[PDB]
Image (cartoon, coloured by chain):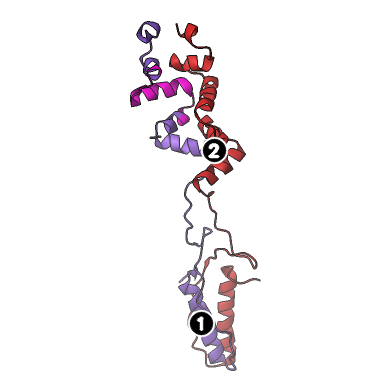
Chain colours: A red, B purple
Amino acid sequence: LQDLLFSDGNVKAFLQATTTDENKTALQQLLVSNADVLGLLSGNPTSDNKINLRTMIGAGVPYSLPAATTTTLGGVKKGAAVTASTATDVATAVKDLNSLITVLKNAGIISL
Amino acid sequence: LQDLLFSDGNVKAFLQATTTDENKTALQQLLVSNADVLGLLSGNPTSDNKINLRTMIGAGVPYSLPAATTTTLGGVKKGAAVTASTATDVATAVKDLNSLITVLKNAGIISL
């Protein structure tokens, strides 16, 4: 009787409660007009759909913290411990300054 | 007449335009074959469905920037201000080096 009453085969499969993946694609298209949402409903959105779906919900991509560069904000590693200076001569004061410089160089806080 | 024409109860509920949550689960299964997409359509995907849905669209999880460790890339906090050195003796030069070391230690740029 459903064959006598309905022409569309995707509708008929829905009414029989047995749909193929192709029937589901067509039925999704009857229910939703946004192309990026249709991409989501397929379970296999295109690259363009993915970008647009994130825009649609205001979502970001997985963020990876980059190392600091001389031009670009980034993360650093924390420098090793450095002892306060008790230098009473120039040679030692210079030794202590250099220890700080190397620590900052080691942590990528300053350039080589 | 629909009772005389169709055997499937979930199809019949669809044709009456009145579906329960159970009818909707069954109708989803007639329309879509991918198990992870069926999880999404339920509104309550399992843990496995969630992982697979993200894979399906190439999405990442919420990213949290970890602190730098000696083995693993991470973020740092920016060090406090440090004055350029005008030291003319060793004691002062060492004092200034140590000030840099403590600043880098305070910001977790180098280890204690």
The secondary structure type at the circle numbered 2 is helix
Q: Which residues are magenta?
A: B15-37
> Nearer the N terminus, badge 1 or badge 2?
2
Residue under numbered circle 2:
B57
Residue at image position (63%, 65%) is A69
Query: What SS does tag 1 mark?
Result: helix
In reply to whether residue B25 is colored magenta, the answer given is yes
Amino acid type, residue under disc 2 in the picture: Ile
Q: Is residue B62 left or right of residue A112?
A: left
Identify the image quadrant of the N terminus of chain B.
Answer: top left
Disc 1 crowd rating (10 Å Cα; few below 14, some 14-19, many 20+) is many
Question: What amino acid is labelled 1 in the image?
Answer: Asn
Name the residue rendered at 40%, 31% in the picture.
Answer: B42
State which quadrant residue A65 falls in: bottom right
- Name above or below for residue A4 compared with residue A11: above
Mark 1, residue position? B98
